[PDB]
Length: 150
Image (cartoon, rainbow, N blue to C red; front, top):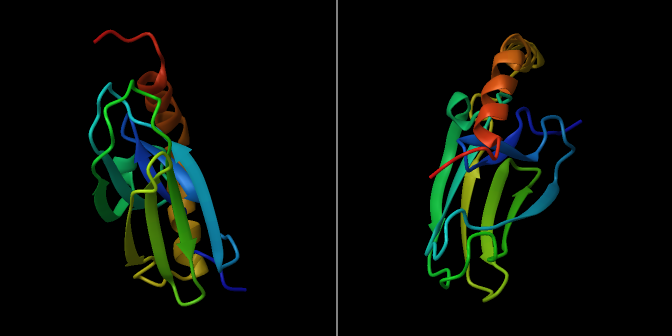
């Protein structure tokens, strides 16, 4: 039963973990979601690929980092950037970010689960995530609330 040991996602504004492939998904698999920019006229988007079960990206493990540059000037939230995670049977994760308005794209290939975790080890990280779930949920709520001033 070949699956990804740990959840795979990207950092979204707030330092928040956004999962693309949940842990224990049958591989090969391909998942995609659409993201936009955070501020007006944002010329590039940062793609930080994280692995782990915690709510905030900083508590997970950074596997990859790259940018999609050359986003044309537009209001925050207008550009449509599709991020795809494609995970093969051989444990190669390809992460692509594509500007849907231009077809412009960047990608990386990385190897997930370099520790090749046992079920015991996964189980342990899951337990620790549960131990911090309440605290994690509270920080996430606070970050994502829209009652903020620039």
